Image: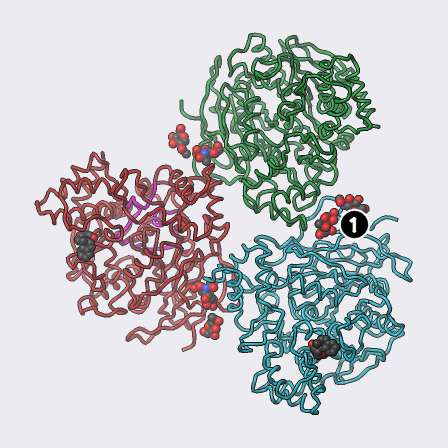
Chain colours: A green, B cyan, C red
């Protein structure tokens, strides 16, 4: 087999052919194709620039580096979320603005297959594109799968709240990667006219943000947010960000005389220096002691007036923006195992009481943002069922799982619906065999669990039962169908009701059946409590 | 009511209201409006670039930092020159290209008031805009007052004598602020068609230079120089500047292989390194020992072929330019106390003698630039009056003051008059009650004295006598009048004759009246003596 | 009598006049005219850029700095090759993109004399333009002599094989200077339509490369390669260069994560650091210990896709480029002393034997590149002669000279001839009197020996005899006749046949006369042996 060579604006790319069990046409794969100029030196904390064109044939045949992040934390999430047999270790580097392509098309002739661009999660602090192999998806549903990478942590979200460092560089990288798709994907058998953006968690939030940004208008045609939206305050830094900026500057050892001075100084530091600072800050771990409101937050999406002209809560109440089919969905136990574990959540006992509950939730303020004078009312409505200390822990996890993902998600879907745009919702409730051993077997539909079915882990890994194997096939159909027509339906698949007034949504799992009114009670209770 | 918000070209700015005794309408003050991109990193030693526009409302409510300078000397000059009750301490920074705006207009309606841009002095080595509060002048004369800052010392005047580092960055910053005003001052109630530039000392020197530069052509319509002009040699380096550049490069710890190499190296130093380098050169103090003519330079205005195409001495006796009304003035005793006190001039005796005189006057070369063979003739002229060891000390001061301000000022005036453009002269002779304690009472019209009257110190500070209050109301009317018509005269004021052929000028003080032939005698004497 | 002053595109240059022995027309000399912007900071490893225009008159009267290189080796080569009486001490700097002009034309009147641009040699690692004084040649043949410089070693040839650092900066520097000649030379009395480029060794290789470069088409009209062509392997690294980059990267102490990462780290290193890295490398010295092949050669000309689109080998077989009169030549004893000396070749005992030869040959791999399995046949061909162990050393020095210069050189001329363009060859067989003392009198026509005749050492240095003087004059006529008409012939000169199918070449020395089939037998052997 002679390597697939594609011609792109910036030059030619050389890839490799990989065949998948049960498919005639081997999939053409490309790794580490640059879509932007390396954000080094003076390019740090600025919008991504076009990639410099190359003279000969570029070998897109080596997994690219994952943006600088906590290597330990990074590699772990890669392992837990990956869908490939063996996990692929990755190197760090500021030089990370790359994207991988998986095309099943026969490059020998013209092809305009729907394109699906994936934005990985990791709370904007960690993650990589290489973690997800788009082999199965491409072959199984005949779509072009593109996994993109974007600036994380300080490198992609540091903001002085002014024109010296607006922020949201990570998000600008996403929009930059999307343009590349529009100008080149046709060379890989893709249809720049049928691009669908889908991500999980932080990636879900990103898709949520892009669906709102005037900078993305016309860059995609359908969107999927998996367990993550923009109303999810945790990732969106509203209010004056200046204070957090100065805090970072000082930790890195810089004067805070003026914004421009901070930025200039941070541009002076080395990758290693910013990483150490990144770690002293302990952004991914939750601070137990101290004041709930003080415990340093983090850094993420901001309202720069470029990507976002205003907070998401506001924007969504404005039906004058360009709309597109939008699928929003959550898992059964978003806060089941994964997240708590990675945050080192205080759940050693496996039990709880009305007191600790009101105490853990308060300290969990940097996550669920709940006023202390509200703590009780909330703690009661949930943990008031039985007296079982164990039944309590579980309801508490639901409590949180509804605040971060449940309520926000349904709300977003509602508004999008009311906006007059095609909307679909779903609740994934399954337990993949590819779960971690340290995961209690009772936890079903945990954070990220649907990833294995969406990316077809069953056709790359081992031990998947016929049930699981078919659950995956089923899901890819849905996703691919949506990608094709902005409607998940297709012959041979359960019927997926459109999310309208009836609020019909689809429950996916062992038995995939349609239902209605998702987290309706939940949305109600919280819409009020928060209104104080 | 509500804080003032003006929309400029680069975005909206938020100011603050301040009422002043006897004025209904409060003055809208704006602090720290950026008129240039912070000259940091590679931008060091290069022309000023346009400021980047901002997405929301910018708060122009804090005093901006002052450009890097001797923190010690800076605070001292500010306290001595400030027209306000309590001196405002400042921060040092390379990010200092800001300006403050004081408009007395009712921003709720259209207004086109005359505009006066103030350029602070400080030997191009120290100074700040914030030192001068425009609240009084704006309220009392109904004009917009704009105080600007420009790079100082190494940062704004370093020159290799060639294209790798022309120099005059500071003057360019000044020209830059005039362009900002031309494009934005209307949003603050100003009339871009009537901008008057004025400054004292180094600032007066700056105004003079701008009057001779093609770069400032059409950016101002009137000009006033308070005790300082172009011929004021000391601030205008002549000959090869390369040697001084190298002296500076070595002190900072750089190579000196080529001009490009020097500049490339200093560009890499840090603010503190250049600040500590500045402190070592001791530009401010006068060296008492070693050979006089050698004594260390100071950097300043240079003939770069961009701002000045030749020496002021050459440009005046020449080109058919675009002239404008020009007001040039000096004080009664320019070297009476303030300057000598700050240069630590050796006069602890309170007396001098014909011999010591010639000794001092020769060591004072870096200030007067008089050949040693001329000294006796010159020394004799002034000190040859009587034998009093006191009357000598004083006459020696008139000597210095005449060579540095008196004669140069009148020559300039004449040259301007002869060019055929309105010309006015004045001589301020009054001892403000806001003078420093350590200042003998025998001094009148010391350096900087007319500053309290010009910016109405009597209306901010305390204790002004009715006579001092009046002197201020008067001077301001004159300035403002000149700024409106280009003629100081107006009702309720003594007649100020034009500096035409009769060489009439205004003697300002407790008793203001017109006179003729200011310094005529000296100009003559020094023209021959200097002609070897 | 008054300093010459010519106006160039970026400003005025002030030179000096100099008179040679009996010439009435003095020669104007300009030293250090910049033809590009100092390649500092980010400009490192990037194509040369235009120079910044200066404002007044620039004094071109000081030897510019030679580009960073080994100061020991650099001084040494300059001392061995200089044709001036006293050697000129030089300074090192990244700031070195300058050229020197020697024009015999009367600047007061129009003048379009032929232009001869000289590219110095030095293995692309060392060398400087100032070594070569153009006074004699300029006066003696009435042509304008131009000596140019270009980045060396790491600064001028570091390549990552991709767009982040293509390479050949040094060759691009040469092309830039040529463009500078085209736009200015006329101002110096030179005809931009008749520019001849000639260089020695590495400078010879450069001339050969410009001859095949699409970029350089139209920048010259005649070319002379003296002991060095593009086929001279040792200077053109084919294959993947990425490794040598990683090696340099690591030695300089830089991560090797990605090309962009490497390039970015090296740009951050100080000139001094990169020189230390250059010394650690140990390029100019042949390594005896270790694997012959692994013993890294150097780093030089690469196929970037901008200056060269394919290996010289492939390019020559293409008669579809621009063709011009090309003179190519070698010296009787190319490897007779200078080269084996500067590299510390193990030949002290002044003799060799078949075994030590085959073994020596294998170690010299990074010089003549000879598959180990070939050595015996090769060594048996040259050393199969007498049993005289001393003759074997000389014949071994022929073996090498042939593979590095003789053979490659003839093949080029032939290929050029066959492409349909005027070709001329020669063999210099003479021992200049200006040879180092440590050079055996039996070595005649050693590497670089012709330089003394070409640049007329006999008319600047002492000791030359009537015969050497006569030789120099002769050679200078030939070189200038070529520069004039693309034909070395002229009245009063031996006939120099054209290198057509008969393959006539000129033998230069004490007895200069025509001849045929130079190296004919040797090329057949090596072409055949190398066919593997
Ligand atoms: C010790 C010094 C400081 C403060 C003084 C205050 C009042 C009397 C006298 O005035 C002295 C001077 C000495 C005489 C000279 C110093 C010159 O710097 C300015 C002047 O006019 O007087
Ligand atoms: C002892 C060795 C080192 C330095 C010398 C210096 C001057 C005389 C002679 O030159 C010797 C040589 C012996 C002859 C060798 C020198 C090689 O450099 C090439 C050669 O032709 O034979
Ligand atoms: C820097 C490096 O050595 N890695 C590889 C890079 C990748 O493009 C990037 O790392 C992104 O994967 O360049 C190649 O792919 C190429 O163009 O031939 C080969 C090389 O092995
Ligand atoms: C550090 C500081 O005090 N400067 C402040 C500036 C100044 O007013 C000038 O714009 C620039 O110095 O503006 C702010 O106050 C503002 O617009 O919110 C932010 C900043 O903190
Ligand atoms: C660039 C530089 O500063 N170097 C020297 C220059 C040369 O033009 C260049 O070095 C190239 O020769 O010449 C000078 O004397 C000059 O008057 O311009 C200044 C200095 O001595
Ligand atoms: C790129 O891949 C091809 C095919 O596998 C290979 O022949 C070539 O050597 C590679 N080039 C690089 C840049 O290593
Ligand atoms: C500017 O001042 C206003 C007061 O009117 C304040 O509300 C605002 O926070 C200040 N700017 C910022 C964003 O800090
Ligand atoms: C340039 O040359 C002129 C006269 O040739 C000389 O006066 C001047 O000083 C030189 N430039 C320098 C080095 O200052």
Q: Numbered disc 1: what chain?
A: B
Residue C521 image point, x, y percent: 16, 44
Q: Which residue is mark 1?
A: B14
**Callout 1: helix, strand or loop?**
strand
Q: Residues within 10 Å of mark 1 (few under 14, many from 20)?
A: some
Q: Is residue A426 left or right of residue B114?
A: left
The vertical placement of C433 against B384, above or below, is above
Q: Would you identify the image quadrant in which residue B491 lies?
A: bottom right
The vertical placement of C372 against A354, above or below, is below
Residue A498 image point, x, y percent: 72, 16
Work out whether residue C364 or residue C331 is closer to the camera in this orientation and state it: C364
Work out whether residue B410 or residue A186 is closer to the camera in this orientation and state it: B410
Work out whether residue B403 or residue A215 is closer to the camera in this orientation and state it: B403
The stretch of residues the image draws in magenta is C209-237
Residue B504 image point, x, y percent: 78, 82
Residue B483 image point, x, y percent: 79, 68
């Amino acid at each position: 087999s002679s390597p697939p060579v594609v011609d792109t604006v910036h030059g030619k790319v050389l890839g490799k052919f990989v065949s998948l069990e049960g498919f005639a046409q081997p999939v053409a794969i490309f790794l580490g194709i640059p879509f932007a100029k390396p954000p080094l030196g003076p390019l740090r904390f600025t919008p991504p620039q076009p990639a410099e064109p190359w003279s000969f044939v570029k070998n897109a045949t080596s997994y690219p580096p994952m943006c600088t992040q906590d290597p330990k934390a990074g590699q772990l999430l890669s392992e837990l979320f990956t869908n490939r047999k063996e996990n692929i270790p990755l190197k760090l580097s500021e030089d990370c603005l790359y994207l991988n392509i998986y095309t099943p098309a026969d490059l020998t002739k013209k092809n305009r297959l729907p394109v699906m661009v994936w934005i990985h999660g990791g709370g904007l602090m960690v993650g990589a594109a290489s973690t997800y192999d788009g082999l199965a998806l491409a072959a199984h549903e005949n779509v072009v799968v593109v996994t993109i990478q974007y600036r994380l942590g300080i490198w992609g979200f540091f903001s002085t709240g002014d024109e010296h460092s607006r922020g949201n560089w990570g998000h600008l990288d996403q929009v930059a990667a999307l343009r590349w798709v529009q100008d080149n994907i046709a060379s890989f058998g893709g249809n720049p006219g049928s691009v669908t953006i889908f991500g999980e968690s932080a990636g879900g939030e990103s898709v949520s943000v892009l669906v709102l940004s005037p900078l993305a208008k016309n860059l995609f045609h359908r969107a999927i947010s998996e367990s993550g939206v923009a109303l999810t305050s945790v990732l969106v830094k509203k209010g004056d960000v200046k204070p957090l900026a100065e805090q970072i500057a000082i930790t890195a050892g810089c004067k805070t005389t003026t914004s421009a001075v901070m930025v200039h100084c941070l541009r002076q530091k080395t990758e290693e220096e910013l990483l150490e600072t990144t770690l002293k800050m302990k952004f991914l771990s939750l601070d137990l002691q101290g004041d709930p409101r003080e415990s340093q937050p983090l850094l993420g999406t901001v309202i720069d007036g470029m990507l976002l002209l205003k907070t998401p809560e506001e924007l969504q109440a404005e039906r004058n923006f360009h709309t597109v089919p939008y699928m929003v969905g959550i898992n059964k136990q978003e806060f089941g195992w994964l997240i708590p574990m990675l945050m080192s959540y205080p759940l050693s006992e496996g039990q709880l009481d009305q007191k600790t509950a009101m105490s853990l939730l308060w300290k969990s303020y940097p996550l669920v943002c709940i006023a202390k004078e509200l703590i009780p009312e909330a703690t009661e409505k949930y943990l008031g069922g039985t007296d079982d200390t164990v039944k309590k822990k579980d309801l508490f996890l639901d409590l949180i799982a509804d605040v971060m993902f449940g309520v926000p998600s349904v709300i977003v879907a509602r508004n999008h619906r009311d906006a007059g745009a095609p909307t679909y919702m779903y609740e994934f409730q399954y337990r993949p065999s590819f779960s971690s051993d340290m995961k209690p077997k009772t936890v079903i539909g945990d954070h990220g669990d649907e990833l294995f079915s969406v990316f077809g882990a069953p056709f790359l890994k081992e031990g998947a039962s016929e049930e699981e194997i078919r659950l995956s096939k089923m899901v890819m159909k849905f996703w691919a169908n949506f990608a094709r027509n902005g409607n998940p339906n297709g012959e041979g698949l359960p019927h997926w009701p459109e999310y309208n007034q009836k609020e019909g949504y689809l429950q996916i799992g062992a038995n995939t059946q349609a239902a209605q009114k998702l987290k309706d009670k939940e949305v109600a209770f919280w819409t009020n409590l928060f209104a104080k």
